[PDB]
Image (cartoon, coloured by chain):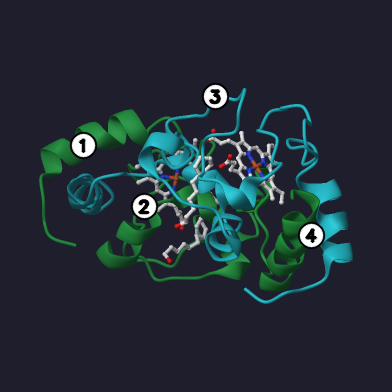
Chain colours: A green, B cyan
Amino acid sequence: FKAGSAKKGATLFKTRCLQCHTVEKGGPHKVGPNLHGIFGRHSGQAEGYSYTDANIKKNVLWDENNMSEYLTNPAKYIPGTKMAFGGLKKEKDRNDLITYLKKASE
Amino acid sequence: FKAGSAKKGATLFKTRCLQCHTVEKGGPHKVGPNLHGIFGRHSGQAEGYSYTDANIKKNVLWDENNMSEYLTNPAKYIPGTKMAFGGLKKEKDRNDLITYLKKASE
Ligand code: HEC
Ligand code: HEC
Ligand SMILES: OCCCCCCC1CCCCC1
Ligand SMILES: OCCCCCCC1CCCCC1
């Protein structure tokens, strides 16, 4: 992370985040939780919001570095996302699948 | 990739893939393309099927290795997927947003 443009970041939040998040202290939850005080806190802990199983599966102390990686692809931390288009968690499942597919497709 | 179980792989296809793919020669397209002969071709060129922009973005001659990685998370290669929950392409976009969010959330 390198410090960038807070003005451009504001426009980004408004057009990319605001539809599911508020950020001001005491702001309401929406589809996603209010993000006030998120950087001095652990993930999956906003008062008054109950998260998916994502927050018992991974747990970070938010900072610029780990949030930058999060925001690369937040959808993959939402359970169900990977399975929706055929994603397979277990490497053995993927081996098994491919072994069959190589035969079934020839 | 290690050779695995074609019978377990077959149950996996039926329950995880079949809803969007067929595999037999001459099989119909569904939401996704028929996969006959997939291991003998490049990605994104099944006859009679027209793909998302994913196939002018990423290109691969399919084999066990690169399809194992694909099947880790296929939804990642569908355009729109990352953006849907606030995903940010550009590093500088991410930098800008975090710079703003650190202030906005204090
Ligand atoms: C725009 C770029 C953003 C940013 C900066 C964030 N989001 Fe979201 N968010 C959504 C949902 C449903 C959740 C909960 C996920 C779950 O329960 O598994 C989240 C969570 C977050 C976090 C973590 C919050 C915490 O308390 O740890 C963060 C940092 C975050 N978001 C930032 C939903 C959405 C959207 C719905 C369509 C959209 C759009 C965004 N988020 C976009 C962004
Ligand atoms: C279950 C485990 C599987 C497996 C083995 C595969 N899929 Fe899918 N698939 C879907 C869509 C819409 C596409 C095209 C995406 C695009 O146009 O960008 C695909 C594509 C593939 C490929 C590549 C095909 C090629 O010719 O290169 C492969 C190898 C593949 N799939 C395997 C849609 C879906 C689903 C819809 C809900 C589901 C479920 C799956 N796919 C699951 C699987
Ligand atoms: O590895 C960098 C991303 C870590 C994501 C942490 C999970 C988080 C829990 C609750 C809210 C959704 C995502
Ligand atoms: O690094 C992983 C390589 C796999 C890329 C798969 C691209 C494919 C092209 C068009 C159809 C779906 C995705």
CB contact under 8 Å: marks 1 and 2? no
Q: Which residue is mark 1?
A: A10
Three-letter code, disc 3? Ser
Identify the chain of the residue marked 1, using the numbered disc in the image: A
Q: Which residue is mark 4?
A: A100
Mark before the other along the chain sequence, 4 or 2: 2
Residue B9 in the figure: left or right of residue A50? right
In terms of image quadrants, where is residue B29? top right
- Point 51% across, 35% down: residue: A30
Q: Which residue is mark 2?
A: A72
Three-letter code, disc 2? Thr
Mark before the other along the chain sequence, 1 or 2: 1
Q: CA distance from mark 4 to mark 2?
A: 33 Å
Q: Badge 4, how many Cα within 10 Å: few under 14, some, many 20+?
A: many
Q: Which residue is mark 3?
A: B50
Task: Judge whether B44 appears above or below B91 on screen.
Answer: above
Tag in front: 4 or 2: 4
Tag in front: 1 or 4: 4
